[PDB]
Amino acid sequence: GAMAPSYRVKRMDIAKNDEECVVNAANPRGLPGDGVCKAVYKKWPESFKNSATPVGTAKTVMCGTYPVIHAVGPNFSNYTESEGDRELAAAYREVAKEVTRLGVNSVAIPLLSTGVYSGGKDRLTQSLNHLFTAMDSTDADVVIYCRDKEWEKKISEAIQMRT
Ligand SMILES: [Cl-]
Ligand SMILES: [Cl-]
Ligand SMILES: [Cl-]
Image 1: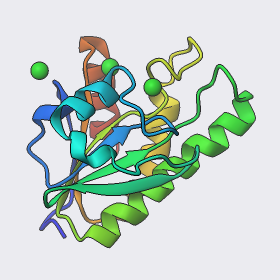
Image 2: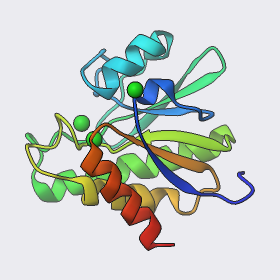
Image 3: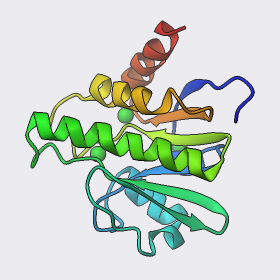
Image 4: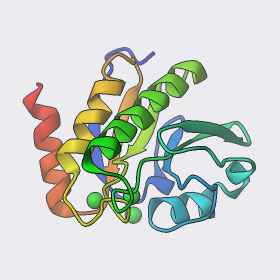
């Protein structure tokens, strides 16, 4: 575990993270995809061997000794708000199980279902709150990655609010 488990946020490509493992915002089919998933495919392509997994689940595949946790959030274009919210919560609970199983002291994590799976809605708060619900009982240092300047400020404010 980390000596004083923390949350932090950085605005940069998660493929350049400084953590002991990475969470991919994966598709269910283990395809290269777009956005975070394509960056992860370019950096750790070996981790996409048998990475397909259903919505609401996470599947870890090692790239050398570096763990890539493929977490599949719902596409809100296809799910109802209610069923999508349940699958998004579930994907983050499966990430917390994997992070714990791996025994890492730190993890790089994107906000699931906030990009092309958002169904055209702002889901910063919804996705971040499910991230906290899952990860608060873990003792890994969590570093959240984002690309937008306004999102960086809002994520940082939300972390600081809990102290
Ligand atoms: Cl960058
Ligand atoms: Cl997404
Ligand atoms: Cl972002």
